[PDB]
Length: 237
Length: 300
Ligand SMILES: NCCNC(=O)CC1CCCCC1
Ligand SMILES: NCCNC(=O)CC1CCCCC1
Ligand SMILES: NCCNC(=O)CC1CCCCC1
Image (tube, rainbow over all chains, first blue to last red; front, side):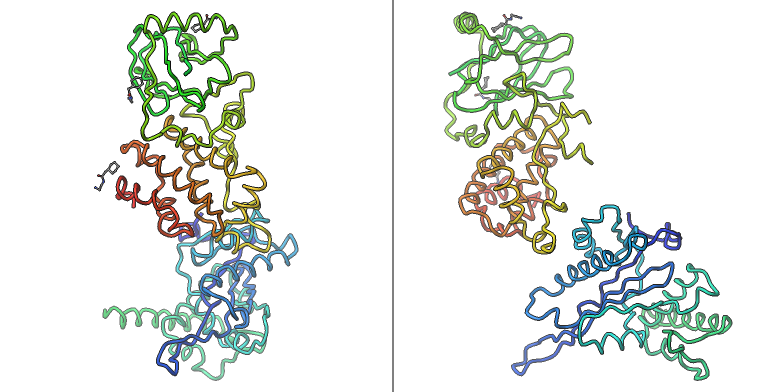
């Protein structure tokens, strides 16, 4: 059934599973027409499909041409997501296919279920966690590959860089969700935190800076402070 | 006009004949029902005064044989039987009509309520949903489960309604996933009507039979089937115009006949609100929306 704080360690067991987040699939800039009406212009989007145990990210880039001539795009985007996730599963060798797919938004359940009818043994699950994966486009290297795409494209990343050499996947996911929650609550401040010190660089083959274990504790503390501050600045506390 | 005689009435029971119901006292001199409308199927049904558990009854068509009821004290129910000796059955029924021991089926029906509830219902199709091939009549009760219920346990006692499942490979063409899920016309017209039922009359027959089993026996699987068959039509953008007009008449009479105090359990709020106000056919069921709004606005 639904995934929540009670069964949270299930994410890091040895059953292959994927999170699917569809919040950046259908994106637009929304502007005024010469006549003074409002219009939208779609921009490139992406499906965020993540193995939380290994860090493997299947980033399917959604090029604006897929919306050309289509109606009811927010509804179509859910079915396009489900079509691309099903296509990804079919492309994986049998022993790499997931046993469970967890969707971050409940409106993806029926489209994914219908597209995965051929896979009756793969469970499609909602979650009650409010995961911050929408902020994936605040990661510079991910945003860059999405906006530069001229055609549909899949790009594979490890969203944990090399962290799993030194920490467990439970700890890596907790770090990732902290970073993304901060980028979602105040992107400018979070990015200042991550890059303030110019001696700490991002390897060419990485997404995040090359922090020592000690610097990660400082960084994580600065992110917690940011989130708590904003939550004060927000509710006045 | 035909007759369903009773050997006796040894236990106190409410007997219903189609939409009519009457009370028979324990060992009351009762020998059956006469003046039954030839040309319709009929249902004779029972609720014991002692144990309201298990409503049960029999679907029959008097053109297919001479049927009677006799109480079995071992199995504890009123059983329908067929008498093969015609000469004798007619002789006994005559005696009974002479002593005025039989109650009379009402003949006026301005409403035409029973024709309209059973317009498409045929005994031969009932007997394929309810498989007991040695009898010409079909037993149904409140507890019998459907084939679809059994896939999610005694096969001989099941209701073999046509399985309808909107998230199934039968319902969804590979490559038309979004199309077929949001517009069920393929599944209605090609799979079910052309493929399985052959025509809309057989579809409506099963829909009407499911409703009547839901209403008369409180059979939950039958209620599920009735609503599924409604929802499949309303959720199709492309439906023959004659079918929509006939569906509106069918449902109108079903909602008209449903006891007001059974609406909570026999009507599915989600299906009816979707069908009347959100579906492709939201504007095609004028008579049904009018009685639904007058009789049952709370559900909506
Ligand atoms: N319950 C509906 C009443 N309908 C009648 O007109 C009277 C009943 C009809 C069946 C014979 C016994 C009396
Ligand atoms: N058990 C064999 C004999 N059974 C009957 O004589 C039944 C009669 C049939 C006509 C209707 C009233 C009772
Ligand atoms: N209160 C709005 C009108 N509704 C009724 O007067 C109830 C009747 C019950 C039988 C069928 C017609 C409606």
